[PDB]
């Protein structure tokens, strides 16, 4: 799996174990992403942090 990330080259091949891509948002600023990359499990969202995860190359 390959996921998009904020730092160049803007994408990265996930190590074994990480089969999900994710994007993290901070409330009162959804338009702007805070973190993007590979992950093992989709973190639970809260009132202050939101997570969106997908499982195909560069889907995040």
Image (cartoon, helix red, strand yellow):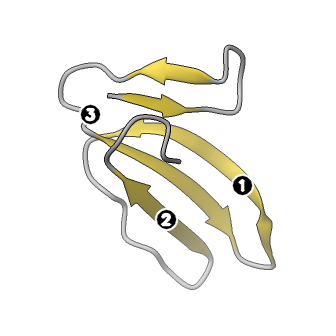
Spot occupied by residue 14 in the image (x, y as percentages of width and height): 35, 23
Q: Tell me the CA gap for discs 1 and 3.
A: 20 Å
Residue 33 — which label? 1
Q: Residue furthest bottom?
A: 47
Name which residue lies at 26% across and 42% down: 40
Instruction: Name above or below for residue 39 compared with residue 11.
Output: below
* On-image quarter of the N terminus: top left
Q: Secondary structure at mark 1?
A: strand
Name which residue lies at 37% across and 61% down: 43
Name which residue lies at 58% across and 70% down: 49
Instruction: Name above or below for residue 45 compared with residue 54.
Output: below
Q: Nearer the viewer, residue 47 or 56?
A: 56
Residue 59 — which label? none
Q: Nearer the viewer, residue 56 or 8?
A: 56
Q: Earlier in the sequence, mark 3 or mark 2?
A: 3
Q: Earlier in the sequence, mark 2 or mark 1?
A: 1
Q: Are marks 1 and 3 in contact (CB under 8 Å)?
A: no
Q: Residue under circle 3?
A: 18
Q: Residue under circle 2?
A: 51
Q: Tell me the CA gap for discs 2 and 1.
A: 10 Å
């Amino acid at each position: 799996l390959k996921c998009n990330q904020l730092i160049p080259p803007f994408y990265k091949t996930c190590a074994a174990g990480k089969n999900l891509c994710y994007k993290m948002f901070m409330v009162a600023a959804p338009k702007v992403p805070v973190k993007r990359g590979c992950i093992d499990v989709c973190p639970k969202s809260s009132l202050l942090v939101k997570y969106v995860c997908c499982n195909t190359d560069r889907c995040n």
